[PDB]
Length: 313
Ligand SMILES: Cn1ncc(C(=O)N2CCC2)c1C(=O)Nc1ccn2nc(-c3ccccc3)nc2c1
Ligand SMILES: [Mg+2]
Ligand SMILES: [Zn+2]
Image 1: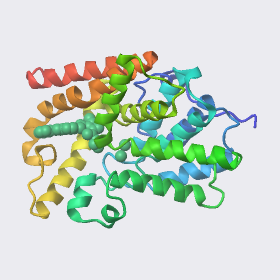
Image 2 (image 1 turned 180 degrees about the vertical axis):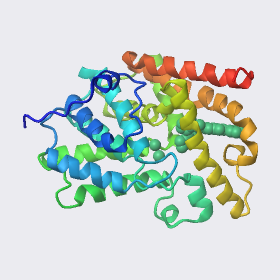
Image 3 (image 1 turned 180 degrees about the horizontal axis):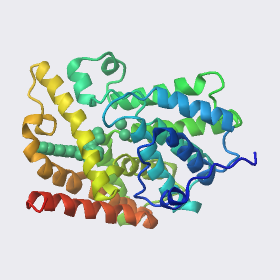
Image 4 (image 1 turned 90 degrees about the vertical axis):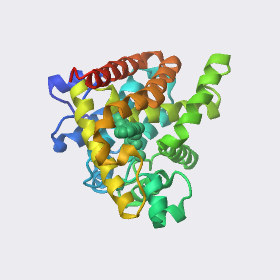
């Protein structure tokens, strides 16, 4: 009850910043997550014994893949924490509970393959879920862990509060499907510009939370250049493995996934910052002004990729 988590001084300060890197010590990530729940939600939100047991079951159901791993899960949660802490009064009590858990859980049991590869492989999950294949899986896994004995972190909620929080988490995890991001942002663009954006409108809140999920999920592009650059190696390590598996199915993979086309990576990153990342944080910043530093960091990293192309590195 009177038992706070406390971090070292440098982490205690840096963790409040959008560009915070959680570092290479795995054993500290659970404590960092709990610290973030306690300041974001309150020390009263979750039964510490049940939280801890849930965190460790979640960790266990992430795989030893280069990018879509336990470190990605905690990174995406930290970004969401920073968004919640910089927009104190905009989110309900259930949203604060739901979204950090959504972020921790959003890539549960990821194998490092896209929805496309599952469909071309004809993986069982592609017959079970026709669209947002892995993301329906990740939600499924979240519900399973929630139903392990002693793992129900939501048990002190009413029956309908419980149902609202699982619906927040479901929508939040589905929206991490980048295929759904493009239309979500165009809608949020029109609504904000024409003036019709209404945060009392639940359909509107869903959309804004979706955009936050995309922003948190992509947040490798909002770190200091060296974190961004080394994270991109893990991202391509998965992409090029998938490319190899595509070749093993007698399908020529897209250049993104073809390790023979490494030289085109810098130009590929540009396309991605211009088509996905910059517009995501642009629209996010218009809806939530205090998230501007994510936009600023993204633009800094675009400029760094431009320098890679000009042989300046
Ligand atoms: C940085 N970051 N963060 C999340 C994701 C991402 O998309 N996902 C999905 C799972 C996490 C990425 C990323 O780098 N995306 C991209 C997107 C498009 N292209 N196109 C190339 C390319 C084209 C030709 C030749 C060479 C490379 N490279 C990329 C990389
Ligand atoms: Mg995912
Ligand atoms: Zn993710």
